[PDB]
Amino acid sequence: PEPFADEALESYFLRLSQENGFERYRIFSGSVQDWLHTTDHAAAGAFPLELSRLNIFHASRSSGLRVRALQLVDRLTDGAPFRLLQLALCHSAISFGNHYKAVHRSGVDIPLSFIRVHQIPCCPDCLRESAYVRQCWHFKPYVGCHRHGGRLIYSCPACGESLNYLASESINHCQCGFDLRTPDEIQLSALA
DNA sequence: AGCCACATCCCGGCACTCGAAGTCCCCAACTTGGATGATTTCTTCCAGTCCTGGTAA
Image (tube, rainbow, N blue to C red; front, side, top):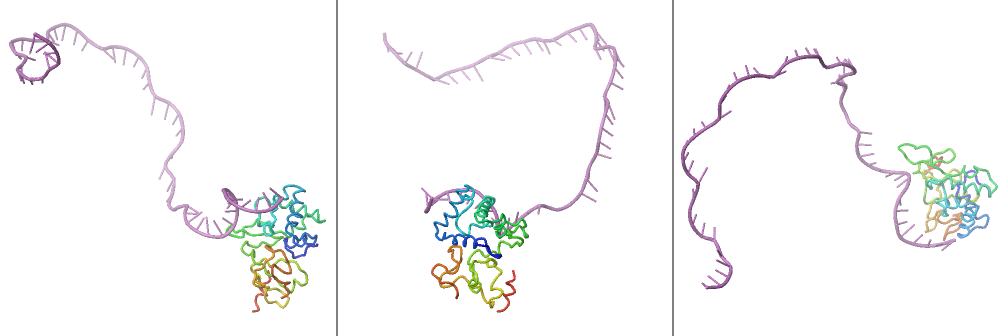
């Protein structure tokens, strides 16, 4: 699978597992963690399985060991040493005022508080063209979208069941639900 | 190899600095020569009383 220019790190990895047929939990644990362990023990010890936990700004001190795991993937998938690292969210070296935590992604630093940790929404009008969870949704200051007739990002309660893509890793549909093919200022607010 | 209890750990939060002039440095402190003789040191009288044995002829 090739990465998209605007793709989240977790989206790419989910697609990769699935592309190789590693659809189930047990093989997700396996095709990921056990292979890493058998390369070297450190690539696995630094690598918890749950998806939310995988990104750097969720991590503690042993980041370099997690990076080594990214580097093993870079070899396995015929990559480049920074192909994935250009996508990851890391600890900024810049305080952003009053000792706040701030998070750095290839040139843009966004304060910790604007990261939309829970209830990621989606836009069916773009998902039907290329189905992968995209970046710029994880931002708190971002409702609606550019293009697509505007309107609202279709929000978490799709059908009497809260949605996201991390506690339940499907893109087109989630849990009990279906394939989701379901006021004129926010399109300016959208430009983050 | 998978599941569960318990350790800590770091960010967001909170509170403090705290009134409000300075008061001199340094180096030296004395040598010598002698301390007196001649005499004497008290005497009279007195120094309480009564209670509180065991054992055998």
